[PDB]
Length: 261
Length: 261
Ligand SMILES: N[C@@H](CC(=O)O)C(=O)O
Ligand SMILES: N[C@@H](CC(=O)O)C(=O)O
Ligand SMILES: [Zn+2]
Ligand SMILES: [Zn+2]
Ligand SMILES: [Zn+2]
Ligand SMILES: [Zn+2]
Ligand SMILES: [Zn+2]
Ligand SMILES: [Zn+2]
View 1: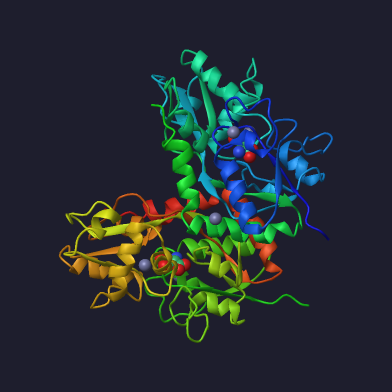
View 2: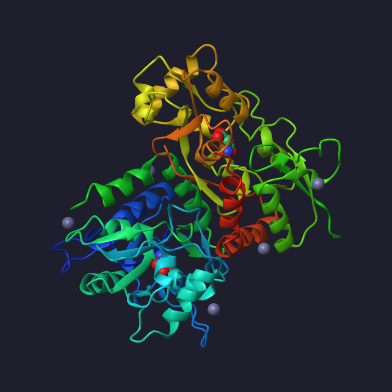
C-alpha cells in the first residue's frame, strides 16, 4: 500500500537521545538530538522512509514479566504493534531475538563498573569480596538479566547479594544510578554498559570513572517486529553506515567531541 | 527429509583451525583443533546436527571477481552449494550479506597494524606519510576491500600506494604476511585483523607487535546460504553461547592460555 510514516520508539538516554535545550515546549522530531537521532535520520534516508520519533511510554528498555508474561519497554512497543522500529541503545539478547528482529550491531559494548573517584574497587571480583560498598544495576534491562542468569562464580555471588539487598540496589534510570554513585561518598558502585560509563566519565562534574575490564561483550541493534519487511533494508543500512565510517564519526561526535573533562 | 550430515567449510588459520601435530596422515574431524573447531562442536550440539569439517579448496575467505562475477573462497562454497555452513573468522560485510546469511557476530575485531619490534611506526597516519616501510594486506578478503573502498583521506592514500606498489605488497595467507614482517628487518608492516595480530604477538619468536588503535570495528559471523533454514537455529545458538560465557572461554583458551611469550 501507500507509504506510511514509520513510528520509531526510542528512550531518553544520553547521549543517544536528549531533549534539546529550550525545545521542551515545541513539537516534532527536531526537538531531539543525539547519536540515535542522527542514526535514525541516516537509516531513514538509506531505506527511504519518513518517520516520527517517540519516547517509550514506560521509560524502559524491555523485559518480560514472569507473572503476566507481558513485555514492557521498547520491546513491548514492537511486540504489541505500538511502534514499527526501535532505534536506541537496545542490547541484542537471546530472549529478545526470540520475539523481535535485530539488525547486525551498530555499536559494541560490555557491562562495566562505574565508581566515584577514589573508591577502592578495581574489579567485579573486588566488589564480590566485600560488603562496605553497595552495588546494583538498572531494572528491566539486559544488565540485570546478565547477573540473574550467570553461572560464573563471581557474578552469581554478586547476584545473590544484589537480589536481596535492602534498600534496593536497583535503579529506574541510568541518571538515577549515576546520581546515586555521585552522592554515595564512594559507598555505591553502578554496573552499567561501557558506552554510557565512558560518556559520563567525560561529563562535569568529572567525578566518576570506569574501572576494570568489561564483564562481557555484546552489541546494540536496531529492532523491528518479528517478520517485519523493514528488517532487511535496515540491516543492510547498518552495515553500509559502518563501512562508510559513519558510525565511528557519530561515536566521536557524541562522546569525545562533546567531552567536558 | 531425513537428517543429513552438514558440510562445514572453514579455513586453515591459527588459532581458529589448525592441523593437530601428527594427525596429517589421519582422517575425520578429529584431525583439527582450534577456536572454530570448538565453536563448530557447540553449534552442532545446540542445533542438533552431525557435521563434516572441510577446508576451503582455494584457501580464501571470499571475494567476487569483477570480470567473471564469480565468488571464490568460503563465500563461493556457500553461494554455489558446495557447503552448508561456514564456521570460520569470516567477516560480516555488506557485499557478503547481499549473497549469504550471517549470524550475529561471535567475535569483535578491527583492522590493525602488525610491525616487527622496533619499527618506527605508531599509526596508519604514520605509514601513510612515509615511503621507507612497505605495507599491505591479505588478498581476496575484507581488509583489502576496506582500503579499496575507503573515502577517508589517510586510508585512500594508503590504497593508492598499495594498489600500484611493486613488488606486490599483498599476500596469499596470514602466515605469508607474518613471515614477510619477520624477514623484512622492519621494512614491511602488515595490515590484518586485530584477533590474528594479537594471537601472533603471543607466539614465538615474539618479534612482532600490534601498534596503534584499530582502523575500524566489525565482527565475524557464522554464514549459511541465503534463505537456509539452518540460519535461525545457528543465530540463536551464537547468542546463547555468548551469554553463557562460552565464547569468552574459547577466546582465552586459544589466545592467552596458549601464550608463549
Ligand atoms: N541497553 C540495555 C540497558 C541495560 O540493562 O544496561 C538494555 O537494552 O536492556
Ligand atoms: N577475516 C577476513 C580476512 C581479512 O581480509 O583480513 C575476511 O573474512 O575476508
Ligand atoms: Zn532547534
Ligand atoms: Zn548515509
Ligand atoms: Zn545463583
Ligand atoms: Zn588426536
Ligand atoms: Zn553449549
Ligand atoms: Zn582513491
